Image (cartoon, rainbow, N blue to C red; front, side, top):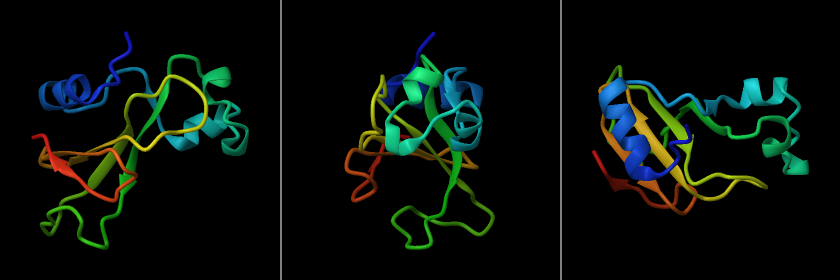
Length: 109
């Protein structure tokens, strides 16, 4: 039910080409009552993590291709304020990780 680690998610993405069922976008989350400054995501959407939004890369920290879109998902989230862990996945399925809020990324896939 909750796939939120870098190998589990990497996994799921590669096989299903979509995020597991416990991910919702910032938008859906706001729709449910999340108020970032309150750190209450887990109170309005228990078991969910933020994920699925476009990640821009206009800074080219990630390999680019004309036509490639990047998406991100929060990793290791249980509750509270958001952490520094993220999964970055492309259109054409390259998978990267960041543990320092996009300071650096590592190829996973």
